Length: 215
Image (cartoon, rainbow, N blue to C red; front, side, top):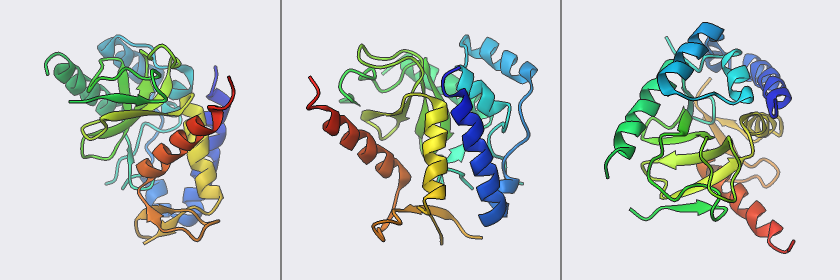
């Protein structure tokens, strides 16, 4: 049940922020998935979705537009999670210099059948949940992985924390509509526009570095 409260609160904030500032994006958030949909998907993949991820799916089954919520990155429907997990499984089955940050938190591999993608940049890169952590990682940690992520990053301890940190970016004013496309900018620093994966990665890196003095 860890991350469950955060998931619920994050979606409240994201539902409410999008309905004020970006109604077009709000109208892309799908209806909940049923427990049946979720059972069928766990069955197809032979996994248990962690509690915060299942709670997120029972609020919105991804996004469908008749673009991406996470500063241009799309929240995937349960159908896309299944299809895309199976495509990564076909690749893990065959054939690059792979790293983890923090070191040994994430397996240093291109692909793993237990890495469940939940967000896509639609260019082969993902944020997802890691169901087979490295020795210093945590089960159901949130990671980056895919085509151009030689270095995997642990970006949150669970999916609820991930969603809540995105919801607080919105609430801190860290955004720009170019409604227009939603991009990220550090408001406090009057900062330049940035790719949100670079922002996530720098945050994970800085936090790792700042904990290093505690022995």
